[PDB]
RNA sequence: GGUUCUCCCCGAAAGCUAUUUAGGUAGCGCCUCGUGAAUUCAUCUCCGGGGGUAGAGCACUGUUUCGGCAAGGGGGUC
């Protein structure tokens, strides 16, 4: 038991993805984003619930019920 | 437009549906990793099924040529 002898348990520390650092890594160039499109752009991607322009599920279905206040 | 070290295993898609949508995006289809579950799945042989395509045919719906039998029209007589 010395400060240069302690070791973490196996599996506790995983490394972490580093994108854009060469071919050998497997995440070089595009960095896992594919080619072009909105999802490849910095800060790109659509908001939660967006399904294209199709009326989303949470707006296609009717609202129902009321909150009690006595239940609280 | 560009995205910087190495080796090992697996390995796509360019389709459908929707979209002020059409070089974008979403669910599903196809890839990967993990966990469960049954001869679960595939090939062949035998058995049980439903077809209406190829081909053919001309009863039907249409189309077509020749012959026979011929109403019945057209034209004169009146
Ligand atoms: Mg790759
Ligand atoms: Mg590019
Ligand atoms: Mg493209
Ligand atoms: Mg993309
Ligand atoms: Mg392979
Ligand atoms: Mg035929």
Image: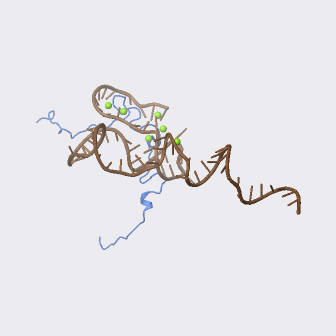
Chain colours: A blue, B brown
Which residue occupies 44% across, 61% down? A60
Can you name the residue that lies furthest to the left here?
A1
- Pinpoint residue B62: horizontal percent, then vertical percent: 62, 51
Work out whether residue A13 or residue B14 is closer to the camera in this orientation and state it.
B14
Q: Quadrant of the C terminus of chain A?
A: bottom left
Label tally: 0
Which residue occupies 44% across, 57% down? A56
- Pinpoint residue B14: horizontal percent, then vertical percent: 46, 39
The vertical placement of B28 against A1, above or below, is below
Work out whether residue B52 or residue B63 is closer to the camera in this orientation and state it.
B63
Write down the quadrant of residue A12 in the picture. top left
Which residue occupies 42% across, 59% down? A58
Horizontal side of B51 relative to B40 (left or right) equals right
Which residue occupies 45% across, 52% down? A51
Work out whether residue B67 or residue B18 is closer to the camera in this orientation and state it.
B67
Q: In which quarter of the image is the N terminus of chain A?
A: top left
- Pinpoint residue B29: horizontal percent, then vertical percent: 38, 45
- Pinpoint residue A65: horizontal percent, then vertical percent: 37, 70
The vertical placement of B66 against B20, above or below, is above
Work out whether residue B52 or residue B37 is closer to the camera in this orientation and state it.
B52
Horizontal side of A15 relative to A62 (left or right) equals left
The vertical placement of B3 against B37, above or below, is above
């Amino acid at each position: 038991m010395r400060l240069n002898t302690l070791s973490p348990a196996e599996g506790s520390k995983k490394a972490g993805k580093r994108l854009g650092r060469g071919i050998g890594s497997g995440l070089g160039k595009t960095g896992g984003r594919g080619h072009k499109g909105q999802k490849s752009r910095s800060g790109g991607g659509v908001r939660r619930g967006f399904e294209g322009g199709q009326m989303p599920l949470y707006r296609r279905l009717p609202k129902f019920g009321f909150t009690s206040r006595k239940a609280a």
